[PDB]
Image: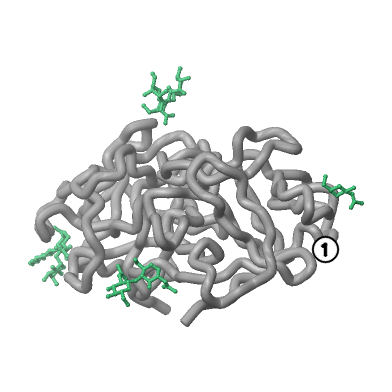
Amino acid sequence: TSFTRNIVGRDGLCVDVRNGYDTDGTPLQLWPCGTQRNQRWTFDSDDTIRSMGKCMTANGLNNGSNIVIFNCSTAAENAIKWEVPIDGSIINPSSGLVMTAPRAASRTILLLEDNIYAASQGWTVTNNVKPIVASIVGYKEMCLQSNGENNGVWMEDCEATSLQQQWALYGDRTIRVNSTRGLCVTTNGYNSKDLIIILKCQGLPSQRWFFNSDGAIVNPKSRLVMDVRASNVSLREIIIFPATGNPNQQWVTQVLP
Ligand SMILES: *[C@@H]1O[C@H](CO)[C@@H](O[C@@H]2O[C@H](CO)[C@@H](O)[C@H](O)[C@H]2NC(C)=O)[C@H](O[C@@H]2O[C@@H](C)[C@@H](O)[C@@H](O)[C@@H]2O)[C@H]1NC(C)=O
Ligand SMILES: *[C@@H]1O[C@H](CO)[C@@H](O[C@@H]2O[C@H](CO)[C@@H](O)[C@H](O)[C@H]2NC(C)=O)[C@H](O[C@@H]2O[C@@H](C)[C@@H](O)[C@@H](O)[C@@H]2O)[C@H]1NC(C)=O
Ligand SMILES: *[C@@H]1O[C@H](CO)[C@@H](O[C@@H]2O[C@H](CO)[C@@H](O)[C@H](O)[C@H]2NC(C)=O)[C@H](O)[C@H]1NC(C)=O
Ligand SMILES: *[C@@H]1O[C@H](CO)[C@@H](O)[C@H](O)[C@H]1NC(C)=O
């Protein structure tokens, strides 16, 4: 009924009990990923998430409350239950608040905050603590390609050698330029027809993505999906647009060697 994984989030760092202490009340933080026991989280059918035999616990259920480790039997029941939405949030059901890394740096302390679907609120429960590196193949079997910081992404004929067709799929639900991992696929607004470009990763809702079961790449805040504009590759414009199920919005990842 239980299984154990790392939890990877902002900038590819992991959820870590600060300094390996199991004392009740010790904050959770970001720290570079590893196998140490204070980064190994056991998910149970009672919706608890445990490390070193203690529970991930909201120290209060307010916006900005700290998340800590605490004895499972003595903590408040409402403070120790968590769900894991398919879009990569980690949510406390009682409060509706979500796990958030307010800064990218190692040693950032994790907080419960209002859900704004930010990349700083995206997490991946996994034993692979390295980003997955893949092509993203879409309309007409062409590949998504980055064309540098501040420019639009667009489709091109796939080629195994193009580094600008290689994407690092990070645990915080960002899609990064593999050769330049400080750069993020970013929608330039939350409205239909806004352009998708590459920008410096900043933890924003504009930089968070979800690969859903219909082949779409969804931006949770806008609700809108990746779309090759007007089904016209020659425009060299990828936008966000409502999900239509059409070929111009279908994508798959293909892992690279
Ligand atoms: C919940 O906590 C959040 C983090 O402190 C608040 O958002 C932050 O508000 C600050 C300004 O007072 C500022 O640091 C940031 O704009 C913002 N941070 C992020 C990433 O959201 C949030 O405050 C609300 O939302 C912000 C955007 C402002 O518009 C405030 O006026 C809002 O109150 C907190 N929510 C509540 C209910 O206070
Ligand atoms: C969580 O807090 C519990 C209540 O304070 C701890 O249980 C107590 O542990 C004592 C030995 O450490 C034991 O003599 C007490 O009778 C017991 N109280 C109860 C109600 O069980 C608990 O410690 C764990 O559970 C006990 C039963 C022993 O197996 C300990 O070795 C366990 O650590 C605390 N949990 C943790 C993980 O610290
Ligand atoms: C994606 O980028 C990564 C990170 O720069 C590349 O991985 C490095 O590859 C070199 C040579 O094989 C290794 O010595 C390093 O250890 C790697 N670094 C890390 C942090 O993993 C990788 O080659 C790129 N391309 C692919 C397809 O993954
Ligand atoms: C596609 O986009 C290109 C570039 O603007 C344009 O020349 C062409 O007419 C567009 N329409 C179609 C149907 O290809």
Q: Say left or right for 28 vs 79.
A: left
Residue appearing at x 19%, y 64% in the figure: 38
**Residue 20: x and y, percent?**
11, 60
Residue 72 seen from this side: no
**Residue 214: x and y, percent?**
73, 65
Q: Which residue lies under the disc numbered 1?
A: 247
The front one of 200 and 88 is: 200
The front one of 11 and 9 is: 11
**Residue 22: x and y, percent?**
12, 59
Q: Is residue 73 above or below residue 148?
A: below
Q: Amino acid at mark 1?
A: Pro
Would the CB of label 1 be found within 8 Å of ligand 4?
Answer: no
Q: Secondary structure at mark 1?
A: helix
Residue appearing at x 21%, y 53% in the figure: 70
Q: Is residue 37 above or below residue 112?
A: below
Give the quadrant of the N terminus. Answer: bottom left
Q: Say left or right for 39 vs 221.
A: left
Q: How is the image coloured?
A: one colour
Q: Is residue 112 above or below residue 231?
A: above
Q: Say left or right for 118 vs 52.
A: right
Residue appearing at x 70%, y 33% in the figure: 191
**Residue 237: x and y, percent?**
71, 46
The front one of 12 and 236 is: 236
Task: Characterize the local packing of mark 1: few (<14), some (14-19) or many (20 or more) Cα atoms within 10 angstroms.
Answer: some
The front one of 234 and 44 is: 234
Residue appearing at x 42%, y 42% in the figure: 200
Residue 79 seen from this side: yes
Number of numbered labels in the structure image: 1
